[PDB]
Each structure stands twice: as C-alpha cells, then as structure tokens.
Length: 200
RNA sequence: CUGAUAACUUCACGGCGGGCUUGAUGUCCGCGUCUACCUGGUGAACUGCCGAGUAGGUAG
Image 1 (tube, rainbow, N blue to C red):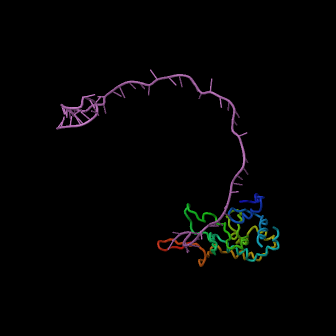
Image 2: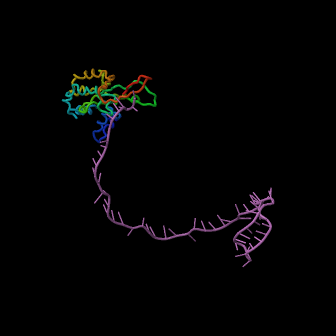
Image 3: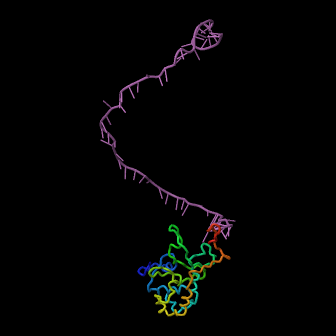
C-alpha cells in the first residue's frame, strides 16, 4: 500500500523493519527487489553479500517454514512445544467473531531465542496486486516472475532451489501439540448430552 | 467440570525564598381592589343560717 512513489520517509531505516514483521499492511515492489535482498542476506551471518550469499544457504533459512505457524501456543505461557498451521473448519453467524473473518496472511515464527535472525526470506509478504499471502505458497511453481536476482546475482547458484520447491509441498495440515508434558491450557465442556470433550 | 488445578512485590524519602491593583460615575415619569353573609346554651348547679366582711365556714 506504500509504493515506490512514497517509499522513502527520509527519517531513518525503520520502514523496512516495520514492513517486514506483520502488524500492518505491506509494501509492493515490481522490479526493485535488489534494494531489499542485499540487506536481507546481510541481516544474518548493502552490496557486500555478492560472494557470500551461498553460505548459510544449505537448509537453515529454508527450515524456518516448518517452525513458522498460524496459531501461537506460546501465549501467554512460552514453554509449550508446538506448531499449528491450520485455520478453521466451519462458518459462523455474523455477530460473532473468529480468525476466519479476516485474511490469513500475518503468520510468523515463534520457536527460539537464538534463531530470531533466521526467520527471513520465507516469512514476509509482498502484495503484488492483491490476494496477499506469504512467500511459501506463491513460490511452488516452475514459471515465476521477478527472478532477476537469480539470473543476475551470480552468487546464488542453481543447486538448492528444487529442494525449496519439494520441501514446502504440503504443510497446511500438520498439527502436533504433545500434552506429555508441557504447559498447555486444557479445558472440558459437555458438547453432547453425556460425552464431554476436552478442548484446548 | 470455569484458556483447568498452584501462585506473600518491598525497603528509605525536608519544594523553599520575594511581591501597593487603581482613577471617575443622577435610574426615573404614571397608577380607584369592589359586591354578599343568623354559630347555637331546648328546659338546664336550689333554698337557708354564722361571719361588722365581692375574702371566709356551714345544713339539706
């Protein structure tokens, strides 16, 4: 929503740090991606990564979609040991609310304190012309645009892109919380007349 | 069968010093409140004597 006509607030560099992490609508790019990804590779480990993009590139930044999740079991008790990436099942009357009424794209990474700097390149949002989602869903095909920094930035060789294609095939259905043992809030209610249900 | 069960935040602490609000000021003119008017004691606590005695004691 903040395009290249007003992409420079000219105060300091908090705009990229604000627009990477989701609490707000996102910025749209067309071909000016080299302004972002020469900082993005140098976020971990500005026109310096051009012989060392190919290090810290094996599986570390790729593995952080498995720990990326839709729903957060660490609120407000952080020792929970989960990952939940499944939206809902059902629809409501209109006076009630849920996380179904609003678009599911603000998902992020909650696993570790030392791997905070590894949630880049696969958890953020681009918003090209609408249907705003994350990067792991729209990058599962062969013919894809905006690949100028794949044909030009020659440090990124073609040996691990197919692993990123085949590793993120099906992940929208995996749910695994384990109640033995953690700090998970668990509750019981009568759903039927006799058969209670211990939901969470 | 309650986002389940459990869950002692606390110790010390000097906002003080100084300060001329004043000057002047015509509220007045006029003005018919009037008419009418039963609070009643049914008959109802008497007749005498003494006291010089509107005071005081008696008999019935």
